[PDB]
Image (cartoon, rainbow, N blue to C red):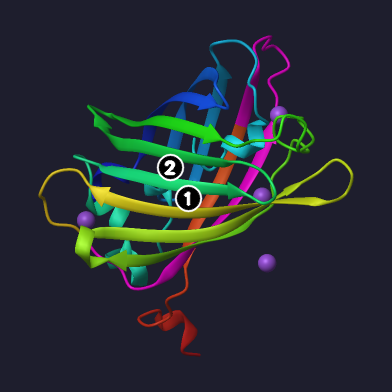
Amino acid sequence: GEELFTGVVPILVELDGDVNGHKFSVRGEGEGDATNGKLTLKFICTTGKLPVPWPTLVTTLVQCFSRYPDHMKRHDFFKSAMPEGYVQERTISFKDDGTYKTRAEVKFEGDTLVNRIELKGIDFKEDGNILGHKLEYNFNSHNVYITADKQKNGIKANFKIRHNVEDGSVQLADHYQQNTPIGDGPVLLPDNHYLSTQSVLSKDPNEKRDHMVLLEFVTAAGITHGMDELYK
Ligand code: NA
Ligand code: NA
Ligand code: NA
Ligand code: NA
């Protein structure tokens, strides 16, 4: 619930990946401040160079750090499933290119929130925008649209990421998401709403390994009832 997230929480991310047979691992470390909707993380490809552009992994690499406004807090499924956690699964379909499938478990290990991920990518073009590394090192802002999944006692989400390509074109990545609580504990199943996300990608000038520094801001919106500040 909310009490686990009222201060600054350490984060660990571990990803094991295979894209078109190319095997890689990523580790990330940082901290999250859900009260303010802010995350800061640094990721390293621990196996060497990454075979896909870092921007294509941003969405896979802890929506429990979203800032839900007071009037919407009963719609925060993510924190309601903590500390036991949830399984997050996605299909990410890159237009005119391959597809990632991801399975992650997000849960507390003591005082650290841990995101452990397996990613499998198939059908990528050897010199498309992904395996050909034609994407700019940046990120546009997007909304994540959430709906309840009563049958699974969780949520589904959908969104479309627009990755800037170096030639001025845009590479679409259609995201389909499911989240299911771990274990049998009660959860909050939300009304439809969205998360508004803004990400800044940068580099550590003192880091020789292939890496990504990430600052993210995430708020929830899309429900107005109960917010008395909007009356007048
Ligand atoms: Na709570
Ligand atoms: Na990159
Ligand atoms: Na838009
Ligand atoms: Na952004």
Q: Residue at x 29, y 43 (%)?
A: 87
Rendering quarter of residue 191: bottom left
**Is residue 2 at least partly visible in the picture?**
no
x and y percentages locating residue 51 in the rendered image: 64, 23
x and y percentages locating residue 124 in the rendered image: 64, 35
Residue in front for this viewpoint, 226 or 29: 29
Does residue 195 show up magenta in the picture? yes
Amino acid type at image mark 2: Asp
Quadrant hosting ligand 1: bottom left
Q: Which residue is mark 2?
A: 33
Q: Residues within 10 Å of mark 2 (few under 14, many from 20)?
A: many
Residue in front for this viewpoint, 131 or 222: 131
Amino acid type at image mark 1: Gly
Residue 37 - label: 1
Q: Are marks 1 and 2 in contact (CB under 8 Å)?
A: yes
Q: Residue at x 32, y 51 (%)?
A: 179
